[PDB]
Image (tube, rainbow over all chains, first blue to last red; front, side, top):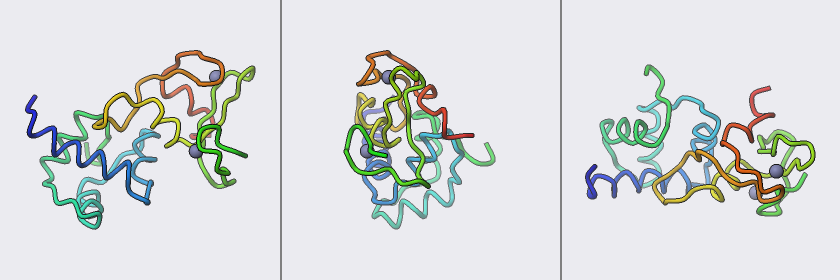
Length: 69
Length: 69
Ligand SMILES: [Zn+2]
Ligand SMILES: [Zn+2]
């Protein structure tokens, strides 16, 4: 684990949980797979720029299923 | 139907958590219940939590009896 990497991972969680659009959180809470590329764009629209690597590692660490994986 | 944590109405088209024990049947928004179960700000998916009505400690999945069917 890295303290600084987890700060960016925390920002992704905060967007998921704080966005008016709760559809991503509802997918996670119902064990429905997320399209990582679509998610990256969704995050970008919420003022959050993150890489696909950051998203994949976030999903792996916090229990989010990825389409194709 | 009223969410038992935020007191807003739960629409007919909306997914909702319920305690799987009929003797309790605590009903609430998925996001509301999940938020009440989370222990740290980076987390998005509850593992387990205590039903606030009956006090049983159950895994997240147990609250999803109506979500998939
Ligand atoms: Zn609620
Ligand atoms: Zn209960």
